[PDB]
Image (cartoon, rainbow over all chains, first blue to last red; front, side, top):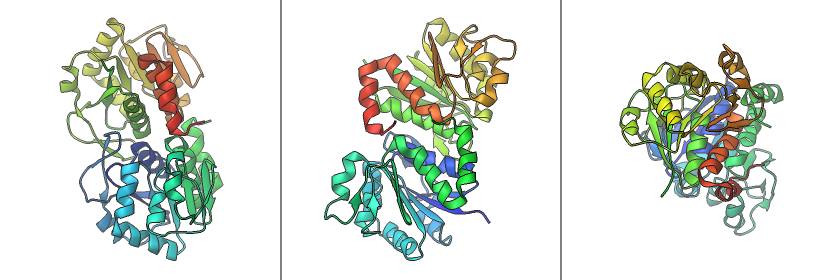
Length: 187
Length: 187
């Protein structure tokens, strides 16, 4: 069967950090569901790009567990994710079932807000470090992509490809990741 | 005043090649208009990401000339751009007025279809080279970003950031490009 990914899209989400992983994972044969936090309506991203989610988080949630739950960054988007009880439940369940959780940029602060994976080595956008480290519940890393067990984090728009490919490797293996990477014309 | 950019969005367009330049240019203070080729309705991109254009190409066109006309890639999207008479007129006018034209991935083949900038040194996605070189109307380059005068081209999803930053430098200068680049956490 094909692995499945849940991407939670909220207003203020960084559109590059949303689209790059969605696109790359789909190139990997992963069944991706772009779930709107607020509902089924179009989401206005941080730089005003408007994306239409495949479904509402409420409905997507009802579609069994996913092999990975992806949290895009963007300050306002991360704040929305952090204040959502629905998101809290989803991450709690994913962590409990030992499923992968991937967050990029300011996205990881949602993990702190919902007390997810405390003790994990994580990274975030440089400007989100202080917020993420409030209380010292995680150990900080400057690696472009950081994967501590089932907690995978990344730094920003510029690390989106590395972040996406790391998720692909975790779900479908190194061979698939390399196959998907070549046509992208990356480094 | 602020520079203005026209991004032409067609069905099948590569969403990463569309969103990255739009986002980066907006970070640069450039007024960007995402114009839908088919109309004002949402556009289904190559990897099914659905983007809502700011306006129709027909209406965007009526909004005077732009400092840059951007053509995203994606095979099906490039084909749509190449078959559009509206696009032909827009590029002809931009070239005539000596305005910048930027195309990435398969996007440059739209230039060939509309006989734009013949004789220019250009690059495209590796798989689009043969189509672009039919007739030998351009000279090929393997540079990740190629800028020959007012014709700026790039190779693929993985060169999108370099492509966008090149456009920013061309419109607003090196200082602004560097300022916009730092927060992205690129190479």
